[PDB]
Length: 78
Image (cartoon, rainbow, N blue to C red; front, top):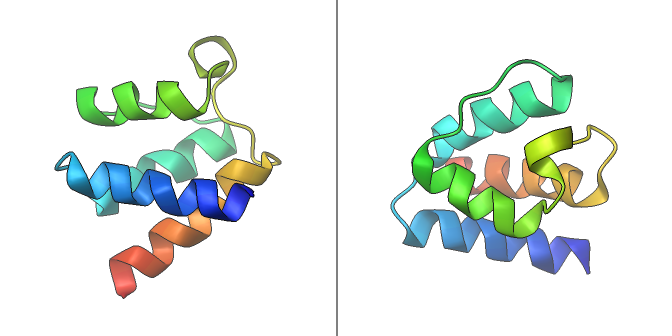
């Protein structure tokens, strides 16, 4: 479920021309509760998948975020 969802987000990021190495850094910051600055493309995309993100950000315990973190890491390396 969340795994398939995460893989699709990676596809969306790549398709929209996002620099996923940069996305990995921002996602890491978000999950640590650090201030973040997603690009316009990333922000637009993440808002579609993390509907409560504007106010709450992205939880390090979020099942989707965790899977996304793994999917992004493998994508950059693959």
